[PDB]
Length: 91
Image (cartoon, rainbow, N blue to C red; front, side):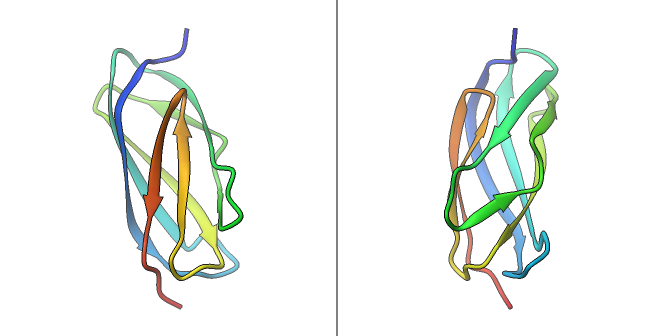
């Protein structure tokens, strides 16, 4: 069974709105165990690089994304948990 993800929160560390993955985000959470989680975002505004993350009990996952918006906000799932990622980017 998948890790149970609690207190999922997102922080966008750096954001450049470009054609490459100019975005880096950190998901913080609590979990019961190490395991694999799918990560998803269904957004007209950002695209995740990753499909899956190796969740650890240390409680942080780093993901990358691309956006054509200077003000992206997008919901990311980690296993069953969902959190909003939001940022003001730069060109």
